[PDB]
Image (spheres, coloured by chain):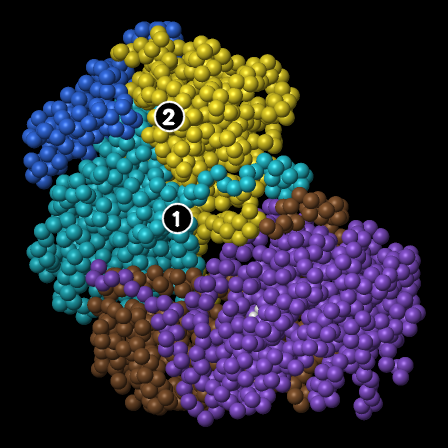
Chain colours: A blue, B yellow, C purple, D cyan, E brown
Amino acid sequence: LGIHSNDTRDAWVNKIAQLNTLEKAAEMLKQFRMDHTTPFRNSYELDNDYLWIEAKLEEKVAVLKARAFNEVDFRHKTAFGEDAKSVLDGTVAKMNAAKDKWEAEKIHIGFRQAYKPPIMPVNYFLDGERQLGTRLMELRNLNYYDTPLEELRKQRGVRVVH
Amino acid sequence: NRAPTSVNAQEVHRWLQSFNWDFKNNRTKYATKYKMANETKEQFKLIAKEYARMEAVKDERQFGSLQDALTRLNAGVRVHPKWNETMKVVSNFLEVGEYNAIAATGMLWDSAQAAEQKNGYLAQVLDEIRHTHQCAYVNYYFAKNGQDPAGHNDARRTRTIGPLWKGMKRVFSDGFISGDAVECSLNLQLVGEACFTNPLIVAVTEWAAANGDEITPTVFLSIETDELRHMANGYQTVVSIANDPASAKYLNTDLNNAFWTQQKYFTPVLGMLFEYGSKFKVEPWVKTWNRWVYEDWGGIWIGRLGKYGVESPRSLKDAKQDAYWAHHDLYLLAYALWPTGFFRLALPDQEEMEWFEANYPGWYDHYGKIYEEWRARGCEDPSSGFIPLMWFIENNHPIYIDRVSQVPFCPSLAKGASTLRVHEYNGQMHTFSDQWGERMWLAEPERYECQNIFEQYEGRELSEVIAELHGLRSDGKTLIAQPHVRGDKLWTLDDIKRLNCVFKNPVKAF
Amino acid sequence: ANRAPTSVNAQEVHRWLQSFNWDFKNNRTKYATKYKMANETKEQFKLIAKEYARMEAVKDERQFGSLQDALTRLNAGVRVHPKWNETMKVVSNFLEVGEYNAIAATGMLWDSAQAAEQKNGYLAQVLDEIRHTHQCAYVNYYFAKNGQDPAGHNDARRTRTIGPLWKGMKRVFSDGFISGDAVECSLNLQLVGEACFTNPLIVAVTEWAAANGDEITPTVFLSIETDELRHMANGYQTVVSIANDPASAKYLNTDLNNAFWTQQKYFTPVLGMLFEYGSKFKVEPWVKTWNRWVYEDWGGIWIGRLGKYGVESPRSLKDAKQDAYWAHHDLYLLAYALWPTGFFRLALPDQEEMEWFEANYPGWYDHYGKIYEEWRARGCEDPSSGFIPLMWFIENNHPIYIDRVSQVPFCPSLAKGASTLRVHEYNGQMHTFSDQWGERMWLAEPERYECQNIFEQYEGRELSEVIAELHGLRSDGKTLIAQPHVRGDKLWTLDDIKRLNCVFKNPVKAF
Amino acid sequence: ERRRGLTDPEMAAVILKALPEAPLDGNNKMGYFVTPRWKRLTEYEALTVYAQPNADWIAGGLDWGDWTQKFHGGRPSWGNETTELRTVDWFKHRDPLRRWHAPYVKDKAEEWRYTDRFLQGYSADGQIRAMNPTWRDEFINRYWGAFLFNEYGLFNAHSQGAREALSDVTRVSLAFWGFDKIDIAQMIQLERGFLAKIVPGFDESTAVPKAEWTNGEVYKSARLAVEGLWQEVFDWNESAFSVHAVYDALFGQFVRREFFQRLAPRFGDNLTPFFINQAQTYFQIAKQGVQDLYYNCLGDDPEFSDYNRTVMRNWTGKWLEPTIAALRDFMGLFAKLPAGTTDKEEITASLYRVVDDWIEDYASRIDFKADRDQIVKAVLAGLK
Amino acid sequence: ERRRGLTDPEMAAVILKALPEAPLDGNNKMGYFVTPRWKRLTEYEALTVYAQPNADWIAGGLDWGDWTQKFHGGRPSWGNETTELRTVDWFKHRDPLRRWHAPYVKDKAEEWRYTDRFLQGYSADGQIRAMNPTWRDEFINRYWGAFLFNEYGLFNAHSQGAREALSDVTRVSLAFWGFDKIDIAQMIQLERGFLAKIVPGFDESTAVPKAEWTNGEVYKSARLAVEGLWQEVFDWNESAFSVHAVYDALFGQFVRREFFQRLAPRFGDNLTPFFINQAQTYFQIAKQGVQDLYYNCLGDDPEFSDYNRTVMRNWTGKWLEPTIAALRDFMGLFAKLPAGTTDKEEITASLYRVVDDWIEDYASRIDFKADRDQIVKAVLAGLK
Ligand SMILES: [Fe+3]
Ligand SMILES: [Fe+3]
Ligand SMILES: [Fe+3]
Ligand SMILES: [Fe+3]
């Protein structure tokens, strides 16, 4: 038990130390982000430790990618072999076609979960962040205060506890 | 063979607007809802050299002042203990605010398209670096020369134990850099600076002078000399986005959110630090708050932006309704949690109780009764085996943390706002203290995920948490934080360990 | 790119400064001098112009930032005891004249030196003395701008010329520093002036000022103090450079003794008067301070160190001990008697000060306290009384003389100290002396000492006319700068002085 | 009026009665926990390090937990996602000059005041009488004027670094580097304005140099490289490294040192070298910080040295080609000088000097394989 | 420990009880009786003017009576007999730069720190690789080094004035001019030491430059003029005038501007011009001061204008011949340069520039009839 060091972090460091191929490391990082890093995360078990473990996985994946790729690939491809530019353009198009703010939030959050570095090159990912965030802020802040808290609670799908 | 001639900063700034050139990718790198105009001008015509000269003059005055006369006078020692403890928090929190202002102004400089607006933002970036180092130097000086160095010398790592630090971080760290660059400008410049930070600096100098502190006036007046340019920068931002339809769509929403964000934390915390962290009182916090918000900012400053569509925040009425008792409740909660701070807190004495009763009628029967009960139970005596959190637990008065503002609140015992909202979303429960933060979270849940102290420390003994985070003094046993400001009978980590106070998450009971 | 970052410091340039001077026939000092400063004399501090400028600039920035920011915010210029404000008028102006004449004295020494290193040391001292002149001027400037009584602080440079203490001050820190042999001028300035009085005096003044609520004076004078190691080195190097010339064994001891007497004759009474009588809170009796300064500090450690070059303690030192006990009490009696001629406000000792005097100077009461109480009963502080203590002096037949050499006023028939008077008529003019040393100085060197004393310049003139003509009035146009008290009301005006009908007389016309 | 606690007798008495006999802690050193780079901790480190409230999941952070408020969509206020380089501690970087704000402004203010005095002396001395008219009218006015846009773009390249830097020490260093860049640009403009003042017929308007920058041939590839470095790079580490360790070090060094600092004296122009001296001083100051951050701390990282070196070599390969192109295009500026000003041998030697300095200072510190003959042959293709 | 009046409760209470209600005087200006040269009295004027305790028998004094102690034989501490020039008020002079000790040291410290930074940049930047070895070894080492002795002699010419000047303003101005001279000499030595540091084999010992100065041919008549101006002039006004308005303005101006400031850049030497820029700035400041003292105050004296003009014309005629000889001897340095470095047309034009600048600035302010053609031809008589 500890704020900065504990059993969960140690076990996850041991688990990370045994990733040897870039494919397995990238798959583990993607699964970890899906399971533990968003409001839409599958479980809040690692709430106190998930950021540090995510950083450790990111370091391992980054080193493995730098080893596996060449310079052009390291600049222009994601860890799974996709073209970063094509992925970025597709995500931006889907966001531009988004109808309401709920879909836009889902698209932006899924993009962050699936393609956050070191999965995607930083240049492409931050450009996508720029465009997607612009769109999402435009959709969200339009008529911000019109919906009453009761209807907003229903829309967000929250269970009112007290 | 001519008259001696030189070129000044104005004759070079005259041609600065032409420096930027147009190419395909000449746009801001950050997400934003507004388009800043590219013909914007700046009020102050400064180049790098002239700005350096102006700042160097002020720096030489302040440091010559600090190193000769103030040191010879023992001005760093002859300060009331309560104010010495208060300046730890004040200086370090202002330092974090200025540091994040550096990054916020960097983002704003990225956003601006006119070269003159960029120049203004860059001048403010250098100014925020200067202010960061000035606040750090206030802590530096009070550590080298003060009556109690602990907390001054390691605030940058002991800030992280206590709950007030999270709210401070949100207002002056995350609210400044996380979001739309125009929203960040509104938090930092339009609201943070015009409404709170500048009158805060002036009032801090007043209160510090009242309590024998001459180091803080010396540093903070020099800090405040730089604020005209930053206020102009905020005005220029609002002007530059004033011609865009996006402004009509979004600017009032952004301004209201920024105002509520800043006020929600600077209403209780500032008043608590003033009235409870000082021996000699200058002015009741209610009057100062009313003058700052309704008079100086809400009436005059916000009125000056009426021509650009800016309206007075819609939550201003709610802020006023909640601004009367906020700092008293926050001090109840902060004293109940004295072990988790990096500063020594003092119970109100008889003179302070009389002043509180005179200025806040009805203060006694609630707050004074609680404090006198705590004193009669030995909250100050290490052998008592009592910390006020024990009283909170015995009386069924849970202490929650707002999921958005990070401000601790006790709805079942507060005199001000006493509304609690608990929601369960995806296996997690979030507690909110007001409707505005609740709307903020429901609208964008992914922005607000900070874990509170009751979750990080859940199931952990208080002494273990204090020991792990280095909340001890140089001797290795005595705590940095104390329930009093006297020099004897200080609490040790063994005194905390004997209590056996284990942190719990208040929301689990639901 | 391709090299390591490199620079050159002051030492690496100073290493070759000794070769800058070259040999030509007319490479000699332009001033009369018995001695020969040997070339190849080194200096202790390795300085070049720019390094000296940088290190002085650091101190200047620190000091002015202190004065302009925190001391002005604290209102430290007003919260000073009135007595210490009046004392600081005189202290600052007189030290300023001392530093200004030190500029010229050090320029003369720089002319005298033959080694480029000794020249460099003297030049650094020249710039330092300019700095100190402007620093004392700034102390007066600040106290005039911000103090409780600007008058005297704002025009001391032209209102000092009314009173008699200014003549002696000029002789010590003006004519002693620049008139005479260059080595003699150095002995007055560096070997005795700075080392014996001015050096310890600056720190003593800061102590007494801090005790009296004054924070401007410590701020400026400690920075002034930070410079004096180099000046002491300059004096030491002077004595070392002249040590091997055979003229040293003939003349150094005579010059040193004359310089010591010149300095002590004025600074023994004046400094004690200013310290003890011009302050509310006392730091130390002047007898102990003087005794520590002259025999334990200067006549001991310093002259003992210098003795290996043939320097020996002055032969007038015993006479200085004999005369130094009551000197400043007598001087203050006389100075108060002539309060209308000053540019500062004086006060009588109060009850606590009278008890302090009688405790530290047993027997002080029956003489000085009784005289002061007689004056206070006569109404010396009341403008409607029509009494100035000079009237009491004339009534009781206690004539006041002015030493022809030192210019220090003395009253032999009333003094508890020297009490010896010499009157000689030479070529139709009469000269009055108070000691054997000044008498010998005049007999050997009559043409060096010709200053007219206030009783000769003012002979026959009514006091009010002299005060008005020399601008001894406040901005009102009728109230005087000098007062017999330090209170805020009942100030004397030129009309009261005119009603006194006080006409100066020459005391030597009685013979 | 106002009574103060330090001077008011009643308030002072109360304060003194409340004080303890001795300080409650013997450790009177702020930042005693900061690891000192040198023998003992400095004011630079005491006032700077750990000012950024990073959590432990950002290498070297002392705080804990997530950010209180993030961007829309979840982007953290600061994060490891904003750069390619990985480190064990982002607070390890120390500026070798140990300059926080006060020393920085002190130095720049000294330079500004000395510049003012020098300009007054130059104007009063009439030294403009010996400067060649053609050099002043064409090369100082047009091409040296056009270089200020290059310096301005390099300055603007620092925006996302000043926003995104993951350490307070690195943030201060980056801000100072960018501020020096903007200062150099404004000094070029200041020299043009001074020439306008002291020379009848000289037009200080930026229209001619700006047209040369945006539409000429000599600065075409330099302008393209600056645009790419500025607005097409979203990595703050890549921006700073490529600006200072690849593009500036070669192209800016050749332009400032091997053309203007070298050929201005031949035309009686002692005025341009005065400002080029300041530019060179700024460059040599910033070089130490660049090497400390990218070679001492990141390149020599105890756990990510190999990866960081691979990334930085990748960046050098990416940004060396546009730098060589900028140099090749700038080689056409020698066809405009009066015949006999310089020959091919002097140009080749200057190019070799610049390239050797780059290889020694930067290229070899990351194991980048650069062929000096290959590079210089490629650049000289734009000369003859 | 000590109890201070400002902070101690009881002592401060006594002090406050003794204070009056308002300042005893409404006049809070410390030099209110000084006649301001400009609109309002300046801080420099207030802190300087009338610090010298002169009596009224020295023009402008406010005191009365004789000096308390005089020299052996009776010559006064200060007196009118120490200079030929007469005036109605010796306190009339004002330094046009408004320069007392604090601003003076501030400026010199700024320049010192900037010089250190520039030297560090120059060495780290490797700019020595472009300097011509012959120029550095033969002209920077020997002749530029030999000029430091000229500057040293001009500096020493100021001791008589520092001791004998008849007012505080004049004394401060003379002291500052002399300090600037010594500073320039030390800067020459500092450059030689720097070159010894960064150029292996370069000797920083002054043996070679000193041998050139004391036994050479080009600096022979310059050395004779410096010796005469230093040790054979007992008039402080004559020393200052002849040094700063006749000898320096012609010979030193030609040596600094027209030979080294002009030919150094041609040999890839951007180091010597760096220091010659400081020398020229100091010269222009001193020139403003000198013109104010001798042409605005003494030359335009309401009562002694004609007599002072006669005296200064006599001094100009006396010291112009040795200056012309110094220039004629120094002309021989042009034959030691590499062939093609400069030609007779450039040398003649530079000589005419210096002579015309002198005639405008100095010779014409006292109605001294100077033939530019005659002076230039005399100087060119020794061109070979
Ligand atoms: Fe700020
Ligand atoms: Fe600000
Ligand atoms: Fe002095
Ligand atoms: Fe001295």
Disc 2 marks a residue whose amino acid type is Ser
Q: Which mark is residue C479?
A: none
In this rendering, the answer to whether B106 lies above or below C464 is above
Residue sitting at x 82%, y 61% = C365
Dot 2: what SS? helix
The percent position of residue B29, horizontal first and vertical second, equals 27, 34
Q: Quadrant of the C terminus of chain B?
A: top left
> Could you tell me residue D361's position as x and y percent?
19, 55
Q: Are marks 1 and 2 on the same chain?
A: no
Relative to E381, say whether E178 is above or below: above
Chain letter behind tag 1: D
The label number, if any, that marks residue B463 in the structure image: 2
Residue identified by numbered label 1 = D43
Q: Amino acid at mark 1?
A: Glu
- Quadrant of the frame with the N terminus of chain B: bottom left
Is residue E22 in view from this perspective? no
* Image quarter of residue D308: top left
Dot 2 surroundings within 10 Å: few (below 14), some, or many (20 or more)?
Answer: many
